[PDB]
Length: 113
Image 1 (cartoon, rainbow, N blue to C red):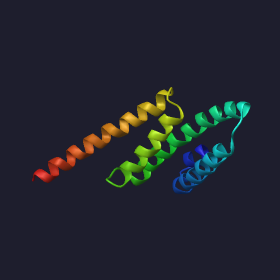
Image 2 (cartoon, rainbow, N blue to C red; image 1 turned 180 degrees about the vertical axis):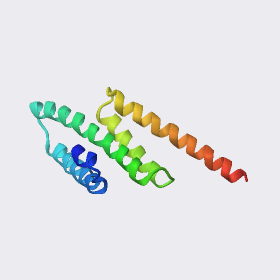
Image 3 (tube, rainbow, N blue to C red; image 1 turned 60 degrees about the vertical axis):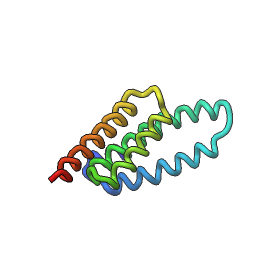
């Protein structure tokens, strides 16, 4: 799916990503055991990478606005929750929040006039 996105097929890849992460969450819910818990850590890593890609691709497609910011924020928060010790996830989450701050500042300036 990363290759699909790199092939310019964006919307379909993103929808597939949503479906795949939902399925992967369902599988996690189905996953309860010790060695299965290790596979669940692997699941968390993979699906946190996935959530980061969901946030990034939704940002790229739908741009930045009041409606889009909550969804990507939710994706990145989920990614951080899945892996708290991944630099990319936390950096992306902070970058998104900072961009939201800048966006609201810009609309403050617009509202001033």
